[PDB]
Image (spheres, coloured by chain):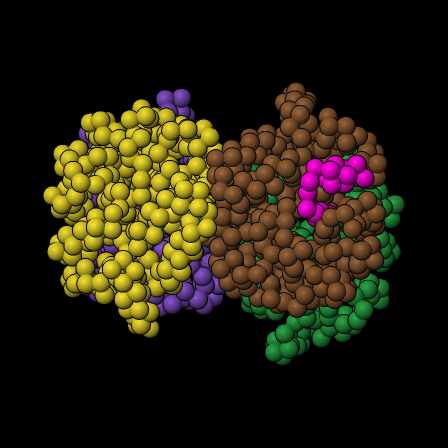
Chain colours: A yellow, B brown, C green, D purple
Amino acid sequence: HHHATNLRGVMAALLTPFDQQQALDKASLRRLVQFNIQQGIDGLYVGGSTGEAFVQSLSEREQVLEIVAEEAKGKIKLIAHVGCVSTAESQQLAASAKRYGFDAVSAVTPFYYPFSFEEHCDHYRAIIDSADGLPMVVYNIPALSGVKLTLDQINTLVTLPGVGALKQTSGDLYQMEQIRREHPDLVLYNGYDEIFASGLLAGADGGIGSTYNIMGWRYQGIVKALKEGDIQTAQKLQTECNKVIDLLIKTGVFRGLKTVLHYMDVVSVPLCRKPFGPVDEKYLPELKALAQQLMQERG
Amino acid sequence: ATNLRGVMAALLTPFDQQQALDKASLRRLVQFNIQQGIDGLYVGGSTGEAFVQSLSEREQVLEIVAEEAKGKIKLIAHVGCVSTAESQQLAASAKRYGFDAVSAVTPFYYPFSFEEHCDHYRAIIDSADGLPMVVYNIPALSGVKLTLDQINTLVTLPGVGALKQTSGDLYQMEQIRREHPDLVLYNGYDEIFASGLLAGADGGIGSTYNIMGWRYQGIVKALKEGDIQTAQKLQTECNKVIDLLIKTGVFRGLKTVLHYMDVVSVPLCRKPFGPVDEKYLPELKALAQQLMQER
Amino acid sequence: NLRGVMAALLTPFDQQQALDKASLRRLVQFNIQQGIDGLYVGGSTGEAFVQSLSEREQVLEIVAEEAKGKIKLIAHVGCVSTAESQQLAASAKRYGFDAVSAVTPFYYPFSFEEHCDHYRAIIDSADGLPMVVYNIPALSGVKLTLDQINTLVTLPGVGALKQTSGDLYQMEQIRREHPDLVLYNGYDEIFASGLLAGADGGIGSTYNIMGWRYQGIVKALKEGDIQTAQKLQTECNKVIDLLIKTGVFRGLKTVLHYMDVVSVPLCRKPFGPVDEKYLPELKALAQQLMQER
Amino acid sequence: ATNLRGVMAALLTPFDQQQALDKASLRRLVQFNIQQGIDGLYVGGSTGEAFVQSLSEREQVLEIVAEEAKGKIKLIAHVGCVSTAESQQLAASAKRYGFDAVSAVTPFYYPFSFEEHCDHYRAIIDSADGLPMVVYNIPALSGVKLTLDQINTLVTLPGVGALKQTSGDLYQMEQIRREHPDLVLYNGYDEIFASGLLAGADGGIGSTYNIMGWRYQGIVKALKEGDIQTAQKLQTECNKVIDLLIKTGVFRGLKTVLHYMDVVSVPLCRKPFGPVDEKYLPELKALAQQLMQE
């Protein structure tokens, strides 16, 4: 619990680049990992939902995990999202994660089927087992999983021996604050980017997100401002993030960020995997507009 | 409507053993919010148990409070009912009693269209005869689930002045604040106050304010001179209290505390609300001594 | 005797949104002739939650003058407030009603225990009338569990469940668990299915236009005329499609306008009027419905 | 696709204690389904624990089923994954084992535009290569809240000859049937099967049919002659079991009953499904004996 103090920070949810055939664009991936590190991001959360995990294989996921150890180990933090519906698939990646040098593992509450809470804790323990002492980030996302944990349940999920943090992809800051109060040293990752500033105020000590792949820096400043006690530009940074977040809801959060990064020239093909479609044409104007904008406010 | 910007207590409505309006306690509770340091009042809301009162009851409360408080603070009158005609009767009555504004929850139970909602609000803003209207939004209890634009359109309606945002979505809070720079934006849920501010609210209307509304102005102060640590500490001490209220049942809890603060005489809510569980009293009893000693 | 096809009465208003007594009366009659086993008085469909207690009492009385000893009359006295529900109940007794009803009190979060008392007080104030416990999650948000349902349908004084839920598994667990219990289908649109899983009746809105069509669904099922039921239900749903699109209450009131029963087809504000463009179909529908019976 | 009409068992996938596919108990469970009265089997669906298998495992299951059942009865391959191409791979495979029908769940987890679903269902029809498709809808587990128009646009995509309707909204079932007199219409919730047939459904695909598909076939029958009273008794007894199988957990519960009837060797579901509770064994045991006789 205390051992996980380091896992604190702003961590990007790495996208997975794909080629004209839907295959892993291995080259574009390699670039993106850099694009991220030169932004000054604290760490990368690899193979999560943003990372398109669920339209890939145990193998394909493992290539990414690997192709990212070669690059980003030692320098920044690496959390490996090893989560599948199957517990055994999860432990395969947890051990592949231990192998490849990773700093922590993480798993989405398994989904589609309605598992009990006892079943949920057994899923997690077994992935920790196979983690061979790597920290666990329990990954909580009701919107998309369909899972609905009480407070007490969530309290129990994070005091399992080997649990080090919480991805809280939830909009409830009453709960976010209740979690802090309860576990005063827990590493509490804000998960919805549209409310980072707000989540930090309730007891977060960092976050994870997908938008960082194109404007990471904005999020670090918000942390700085709060440390400082400068409530004013903190809100300027939240506010500008959501004008981008606003547009990435309109286009498609993944195919938007990728159709951006194609303009920043870090992706040969901005595609997501089927069944996800191509971005609609008329956004290209503004998408082209946003890459062009974002490159200059950094440099 | 900067006059409306503020920490407004959602006034509770006192009853007696026989479930009758307790006007002694109404008046005291009104004074105990003045002396406490509140910017204003929001009378006859959900928190005031509006929907277990008759119109005549909601009128006698309005009248008393303007009697005790007009000129002394801002007063908003929640005049909302499911019926437009009931709602207008109360708008007229609020205007009569000298109120600064009126408010009305989205009308509920039956499905109404968004056009029908707006006409509801047009009709009310009119019987209100010049009072500016606070649109009242509480989706979890109303069951009305408004989009963003729809909410942009309700707030530009003729003679709408403010939005009570009783929502937990601090993304939508920002999108309103960023799209209506001037708008008086009230935070609804007491437990995200600090963060609702950050997201872009300029104040709040809240039920627990009735017992520790300094702690929420104390939140506002703390945030304005960048003392995050006192602010978070407050919210935290607010939620500590909100955790107990959520367990005891919030209105009856809140009243039972004022019953130990000697303000309210019978700590009842109306049937079918029940009494507070006898087991919770020492914790409420000593929340009050605790709280009386902080003020 | 509470068992049957029991039409949820609409409250016809005049051009000033006041109780159109003549039409009210014309609708009691216009229903009475359809075969309907009874009329459900002052429920949601009766626009009750946009009337004062007086106006609701006004209806209970008028109707009970047009109807008592002829058909079954059920009085929905439910408000959010227990005291107010109690009043409408004692009235329903005075006017000599067959049963009272009371939808789970809504808006505020009440405990199931708190609910239970609500009904205990209303069963006392109805002074020996039986209660129709009136479930409706969609509109009230009250999300009842089977176990909670089980105690409520066996509170001493209660005698029936208005099961306004499209969950036909739960219908059967209830028929199973209380084999005698009277239990009304609430969705007009799954009535056929609902008797199949074990409702033995319906309290419904759209019965005000076609009680017989529903009655003849009950016939066919009873008579194993499975082909018939469907045919009917399908024509009973081709309307419900229409009415859902029109505005339902207004839709029905209008149809009763083009049937010469209701002088002015209006609901109270905030329900506005029926769009103009849907008047032809409603008129055609009206003039297709008088043909049958 | 009128030939696809009927009561189909949603096939369970037997596993051993290593969580490896138990191939001798698969074939047995297939033979037990055939011997039982079934019109056909629906393979590697949610009931088949699809979403905890790999593509390989899903393919090896199918193969065993088509070796054992093709010709004899009707065969539907649930080839649905989140990814279109994985569905596409399972699709062609499904055709190599000479299946009658292909199926796929509306892709889940990520929110997909309706358009993006329609294409997905086309790409799988292409690969199905002449095998009809069974649009499989199940809002409760998928979180995909399809409307009426949307659904009508699906089931008229060219190639689609069935809808699996695992939605408990029997008004929607009538609208779909009123609009589509010839569409095969599989009831998906076993606990409202009678009521769903009355609403429109002419077929069924379900998990409980693995232990009492004859009861379900009798409902179709009972109904069609106009014997409501037995349809009723049947559905009420079908429902008595589901009460049971919900308490224990449904797949494992069923795997247990199936174990007692000498069909499945090890009644395990793949983690994170837990084992069934020891306390429920008496009654689960007791249910098997009841059903073998009946």
Identify which residue, B168 or A223, lies in the foreground. Answer: A223
Side of C15 where C253 appears, left or right: left
- For the C terminus of chain B, the image quarter is top right
B184 relative to C120, above or below: below
Q: Residue at x 37, y 62 (%)?
A: A247
Residue drawn 77% across the image and 31% down it: B263
Residue D40 is situated, as x and y percent measured from the top left of the image, at 29, 50
Q: Position of residue C207 (x, y in %)?
A: 67, 60
Please state the horizontal and vertical placement of residue A136, each as a whole percent of the image.
28, 32
Quadrant placement of the N terminus of chain B:
bottom right
In front: A59, or D293?
A59
Taking the spot 69% from the left edge, 40% from the top edge, the residue there is B37
Q: Is residue D230 visible?
A: no
Say which of D85 and D281 sits in front.
D85
Question: Relative to residue C277, is residue C21 drawn left or right?
Answer: right
User: Is A254 one of the magenta-colored residues?
Assistant: no
Magenta-span inclusion, residue B30: yes
Residue A121, image x, y percentages = 34, 29
Q: Which residues are magenta?
A: B27-47
Determine whether, in the image, residue C148 is placed left or right of residue C99: left
Q: Residue at x 24, y 60 (%)?
A: A299
Relative depth, front residue between D53 and D108:
D108
Q: Is residue C15 visible?
A: yes
